[PDB]
Amino acid sequence: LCFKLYAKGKHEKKTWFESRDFCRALGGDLASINNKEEQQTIWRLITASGSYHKLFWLGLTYGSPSEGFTWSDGSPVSYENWAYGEPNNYQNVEYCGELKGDPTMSWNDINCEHLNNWICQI
Ligand SMILES: CO[C@H]1O[C@H](CO)[C@@H](O)[C@H](O)[C@H]1NC(C)=O
Ligand SMILES: [Ca+2]
Image (cartoon, rainbow, N blue to C red):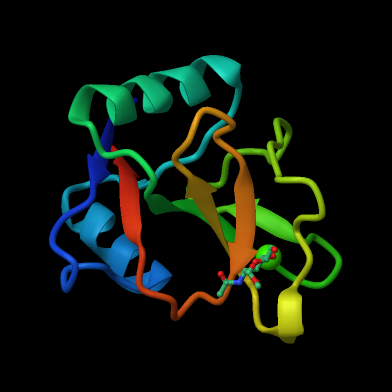
């Protein structure tokens, strides 16, 4: 699968659901990061674009209470790269996952209605 960053204007950021709909409209989905190689591919997209210091929606979304986090594309949640202390469901409203687009490439759970950049896979 091919990944593509979407870090548009400051008023072009999207909720998790709007970002998923955008990627699905292209025939793909929000990106799942399934291993270190896919993580490095995305990091290199960030360096190539110069889109540093940005947060991006990934396909991480909470399933049932039993399952916890899932990938929107159905991939197994095997590889994980949560930031230390995450996921923390801060204030009980954080059911989607974002990438901090810095060298750590770490994940954080946040409120799905937050406006973020996003990464598609196609
Ligand atoms: C203060 O909360 C923020 O930072 C913590 C980690 O310190 C994060 O866990 C938390 O998700 C994040 N919330 C938002 C809206 O970005
Ligand atoms: Ca969090």
